[PDB]
Amino acid sequence: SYVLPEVICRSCNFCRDLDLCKDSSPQWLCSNCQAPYDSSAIEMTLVEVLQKKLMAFTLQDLVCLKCRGVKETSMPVYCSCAGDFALTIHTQVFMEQIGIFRNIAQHYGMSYLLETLEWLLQKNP
Amino acid sequence: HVFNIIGAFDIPRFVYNSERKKFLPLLMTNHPAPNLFGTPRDKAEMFRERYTILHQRTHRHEFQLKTIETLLGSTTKIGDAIVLGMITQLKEGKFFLEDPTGTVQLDLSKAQFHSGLYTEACFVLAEGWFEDQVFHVNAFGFPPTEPSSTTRAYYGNINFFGGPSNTSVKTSAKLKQLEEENKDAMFVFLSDVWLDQVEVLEKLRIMFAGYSPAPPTCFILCGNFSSAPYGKNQVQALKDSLKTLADIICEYPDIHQSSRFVFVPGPEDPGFGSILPRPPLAESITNEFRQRVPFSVFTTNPCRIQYCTQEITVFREDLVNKMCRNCVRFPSSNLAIPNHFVKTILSQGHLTPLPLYVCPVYWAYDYALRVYPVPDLLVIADKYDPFTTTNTECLCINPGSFPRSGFSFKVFYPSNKTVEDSKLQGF
Ligand SMILES: [Zn+2]
Ligand SMILES: [Zn+2]
């Protein structure tokens, strides 16, 4: 499953988290009123989620494998030890995110999200 | 071969070899290729290369530099020492100097600065004395800027810029010929072209009408193509806007048939605009426009334009405010901010001489944000006031925000490297 924190219903203003895998009918209805959520909006929010996470990845802290010390400088390739620095936000976990998002897009006709995903994949052979 | 548009992700990657002392093509080395999601090592190389390109360049200008490990080692007070390093603020108000060999606590409380905009992550030549694990700086300066002619003299004719050619275009007597003959060649630069605003569209009309009798070679329209990136639905609003732009361009056949259009996206436009280099607007968004205006290309940001023997680098970013918000201090008012600004960009030989948290960059792709060798024209489209300056043989301009500068824009005649201005506020 995949939930979007507090999506707002443009028809009645009812706010609630939305589970995209568990709350389909291919559409998403508001819980309070039964107005369908604007797929267009969902698509864009998903895209922003990719951005926010792509940003988190780019600015992520780096940890030493020997000591659990967070890197505090920019150039060192190794630690005060001789330990190696490791990602605190993993590539693998990001790809999985893309797999989920790629699925939702394939199933809900979100060509834009497919495009961004595809680019995001093309630039990572 | 006469007019090419080079995207950030197509910039030929070269790796400096401290041994052979030369720049080698990526595949000619054992250096891993770039990917959007890099490794922790890549994140480190980013700043190492930034330091290395400056070091190599600085070592040729000629003073005796000392590395940081040299200082941190010594058991005595080192009275005089000049070090090339990157300024970092590890703690608030606490500055350090870093290089491949190490980091050292800095005492800049009594330091003087040469001209320039000194910011966190800038590489500098720090002169002073060292004692008890602290580097007391007397003067800060930037590594001397090396002009194109000099870089070309040392390295040859490697095509660092990119594009069709496999050799520098500044070495093509043929293109030089064409360049000087086409005296009417002209490039128009605009920024923040908010297509959703009626007044912006009306002024674009006036520009197209006014240019009909003499259509420019190219119109470089820069990013943030919407005054409102909050939206009732962003991507569709942008698509609609482009329809209107296409309609207006088609109403001026003289422009439609002669002028090329280049769209450099801004940090607020659809796509992953907040991480650099950023890709062009999605093709789904521009297909329709490109069908009506075939002479257009939606490129990356930054992007490079090659025209005959001239290199033009274009970058859309509200860079000046970022630099100011991260300054070590305010430069002296005896020199205008754009002059300090340009000295910084060229001296750093990089578009974003700032920390990653300030200017996010795909680690493996930092080399694409390089401004070295120095180009003929550097365009930093910024929301900051427009300006034209000239540093180290390089013309650096900012057309400013079209809707907010009284509808001002810049013109560049390549034939004799002349820059002109226009303002349509009064219409
Ligand atoms: Zn509702
Ligand atoms: Zn460690």
Image: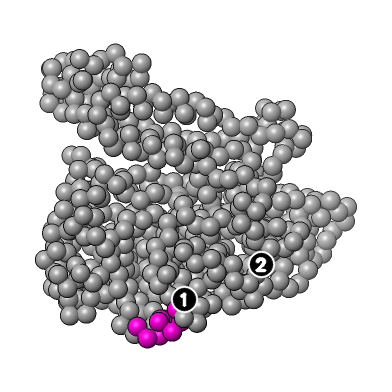
Tally the marks: 2
Q: Chain of mark 2?
A: B
Q: Residues within 10 Å of mark 2 (few under 14, many from 20)?
A: some
Whether tag 2 and tag 1 are in contact, CB under 8 A, the answer is no
Quadrant housing the N terminus of chain B: bottom left
Amino acid type at image mark 2: Arg
Horizontal arrangement in the rendering, residue B177 relative to residue B140 (left or right): left
Q: Is residue B302 magenta?
A: no
Instruction: Give the label on residue B94, or none.
Output: none
Amino acid type at image mark 1: Thr
**Magenta residues (range):** B175-182
Residue A47 versus residue B317 in the image, above or below: above
Distance from disc 2 to disc 1, alpha carbons, whole Å, reads: 23 Å
Residue B277 versus residue B129 in the image, above or below: above
Counting from the top left corner in percent of width and height, residue B160 is at 55, 64
Label 2 SS: helix
Counting from the top left corner in percent of width and height, residue B79 is at 82, 64
Q: Residue at x 73, y 32 (%)?
A: A83
Examine the image and state in which quarter residue B251 appears: bottom left
**Residue pointed to by mark 2:** B57
Quadrant housing the C terminus of chain B: bottom left
Counting from the top left corner in percent of width and height, residue B309 is at 46, 76
State yes or no: Cβ of the residue under disc 2 lies below 8 Å from any atom of ligand 2.
no
**Residue pointed to by mark 1:** B309
Horizontal arrangement in the rendering, residue B64 relative to residue B320 (left or right): right
Magenta segment, principal secondary structure? Answer: helix
Counting from the top left corner in percent of width and height, residue B23 is at 65, 61
Q: Residue at x 24, y 43 (%)?
A: B235
Q: Residue at x 47, y 28 (%)?
A: A95
Q: Chain of mark 1?
A: B
